[PDB]
Amino acid sequence: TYVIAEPCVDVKDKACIEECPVDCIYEGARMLYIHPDECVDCGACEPVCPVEAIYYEDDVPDQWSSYAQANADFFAELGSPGGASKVGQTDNDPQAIKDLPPQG
Ligand code: F3S
Ligand code: F3S
Image 1 (cartoon, rainbow, N blue to C red):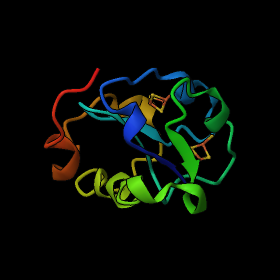
Image 2 (cartoon, rainbow, N blue to C red; image 1 turned 60 degrees about the horizontal axis):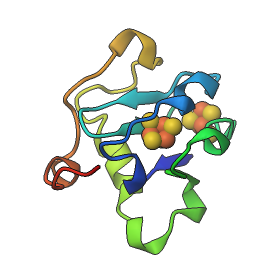
Image 3 (cartoon, helix red, strand yellow; image 1 turned 90 degrees about the vertical axis):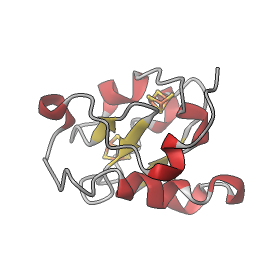
């Protein structure tokens, strides 16, 4: 899977959502989140992010290493809807991301 990390927080450019063939990038209040059970490693999202927030799981930097679990935790109550388009923005951000001070 690919992973959205800290640079997305309170930026949310949303260039990435255009590119994903399976529509598995979902919007929270603070950032977007890649569904790890829906992502099939197409990689089309990663080049388009203007703040380089997106990484393949194995390439997520140590300083943001907790963001992979955060992406999974976003879907605790959503399950696997099988497409972000119908869900829209939801207030499902995990505690760890909710607690970050305002950025940008
Ligand atoms: S800021 Fe976020 S919303 Fe997508 S284009 Fe970059 S990951
Ligand atoms: S384009 Fe979609 S399939 Fe995964 S690698 Fe990016 S979220």
